[PDB]
Image (cartoon, rainbow, N blue to C red; front, side):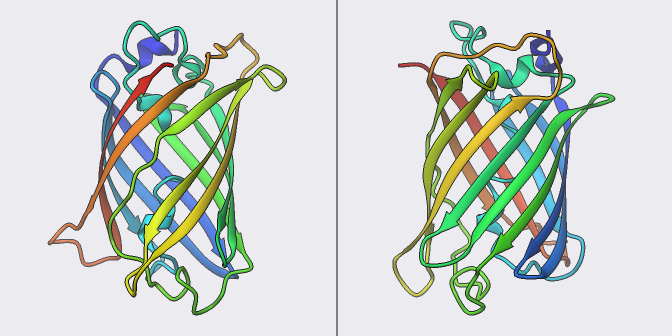
Length: 224
């Protein structure tokens, strides 16, 4: 079982390769997750200079396998059971009245490290819109993720809207669509529908001079 891979604290690596309106960038993240409580702690750095988009627009993109599934559901855990070969995660994120991100990631074990490796392409952005103009507040409004099995692709899908507060007033919608499929060929748990509930806290490291995001996340799964 891939589920056994998550009994203790697990090192996490994130690597993101981005391109938004031709503005190219890289982000690296490091930390650890504990699926027993469903806690993640990570620090992310824009390794290429100034991040050309707001940090909060990347949070969703930057490991639902760390969600705390209570043991009446350890049979509905697609994400952990795909491990260690892992799973592909694909999204299109539509920023209302602005551009969209398309993301492809592979989440898998490498040695003892859970690695989330992402390619992101963003197109059609307004150069002085909320995103490329950096007009979004540095905070987070989490949303549940209603996960639905998809027996046609041996995978899962979900659609949800994320709310980004705009510094000058009002809210910038980020409309998420998501599909995941296993990377291996072994059988995988297709879960019955359920929720993932998330609480994100974004902060800064006072000693960190580079552009960065400290992120602390708590995540649990629930049925009905």
